[PDB]
Image (cartoon, rainbow, N blue to C red; front, side, top):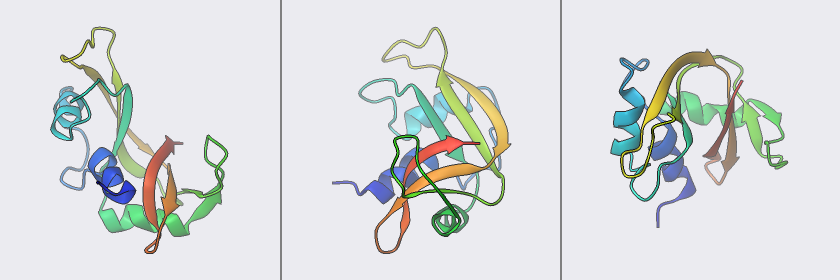
Length: 124
């Protein structure tokens, strides 16, 4: 089955674009990455950076995750991100999202050897 590292890339990386280009970014990306297939995932962040720059966060500032785990890390730098969250009208299978552009630090949980992101915790 899909590894946690691979699921992170599928759910959260978009190295193909610099930022969200329209209000439909989330609607399109949530669908294309299969985040709406079984249910409408309610919130999701995409990171518009190279994969290596995001993986490097695992050697940046350690911080406890929301859930208390101690394998979270905050990026030293801000990154281009898109926040996606359901609109009031979202209703499966017609999942619908508000797209919000931002430049924020990211917090990710890391595991493995190589030690890489497995979960997106927060934009801060």
